[PDB]
Amino acid sequence: RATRAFSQIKDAMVFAFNLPAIVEGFDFELIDQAGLGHEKLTQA
Amino acid sequence: TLGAAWGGSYVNDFIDRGRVKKVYVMSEAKYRMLPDDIGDWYVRAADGQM
Image (tube, rainbow over all chains, first blue to last red):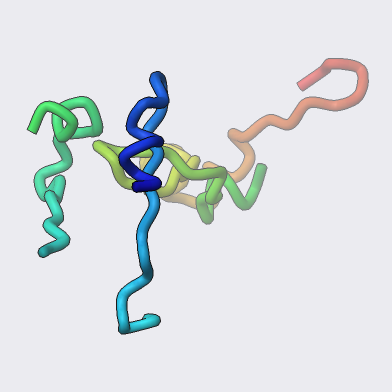
């Protein structure tokens, strides 16, 4: 419900959640190996 | 002057293609290869004179 309401707020990313049963899906990285520089990795 | 010319001196760091590396100042080889080359180096005194 909370999220549902907060979605109404323009000009912001607001959402609410529970922290998972582990107090301490994926996470994919993208490495600049050959030293191409920030705007090129942006593009990548 | 002695040290930087003859030993080389680590000034500060620069970025080379996204990666930090050293900046070294030091004499060209020919100007530090021999004992008589020692005299060839000038230092500026307080009256602006070499």
